[PDB]
Image 1 (tube, rainbow over the protein chains, first blue to last red):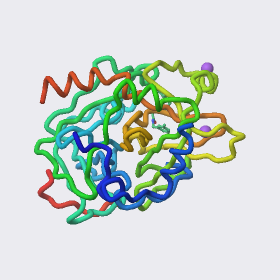
Image 2 (cartoon, rainbow over the protein chains, first blue to last red):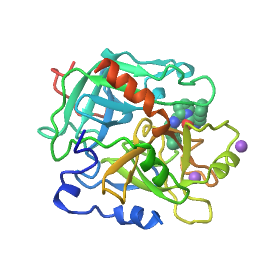
Image 3 (cartoon, rainbow over the protein chains, first blue to last red):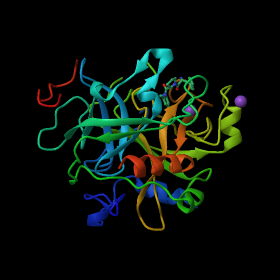
Length: 28
Length: 251
Length: 11
Ligand SMILES: Cc1cccc(CNC(=O)[C@@H]2CCCN2C(=O)[C@H](N)Cc2ccccc2)c1
Ligand code: NA
Ligand code: NA
């Protein structure tokens, strides 16, 4: 939908999950 | 999932459980892509070599789950299938080419902190993110090892692997409708999907809009987390036209 | 069968 991929308990609250940084770091 | 970690609450609100009515059991993973459409792997529903051919009435969709076995009262929502759509050229005979199916829910599910759709990639996100080395994330209630069942949703980050490494890792003929992910034997780290993880989502967090996209579907592997072997995922973007078409036509 | 019973309604 239009809100797809934004998680209520993480992105919508500007909270991160414990390992999403690992993905970011790999998007080199 | 092998060598993964427990999911955080709400970490994967698109995660869906394909559940068998009788005998009540998990059949597969899947993903929520809207309030009435669940994406899964074709082989979850149809795989004649194992005498598998599920009809709508055989299944329930459990959305919002965390625990593997528990009824998560006030949290999960269980949905009924209105219609299942399998890719007309799903290749169950040889290599699970085009290993993808859609499931239409009877009634829409209500979004919540625990239930929320993942995006489907456009060509540009696909092109930008589906690169060797880039890591995606896979989730499921499947086996913890090749030879076992997790108490909660398992999560594992795995790097996409070079197409030739993919090809050189197996005797199965791989196609452009697949990609492989997993660490190389000397990268030390490991982890993989396993039995029961099927039809679950391979997702990546786009660094451009901070949105989670489903780039893959857990499709096949030879064993689980075997060294020099890689998990194979249905390339969602490559089959997107079929996805949109089925959704546009049937609602 | 190691699954908690879901409400009979769902089926
Ligand atoms: C990424 C991953 C890892 C481990 C298991 C899976 C679940 N997929 C499966 O178990 C599927 C279903 C039929 C056999 N298959 C497999 O993964 C087979 N072991 C390999 C295969 C591949 C193509 C055609 C036939 C057999 C997925
Ligand atoms: Na090969
Ligand atoms: Na491996």
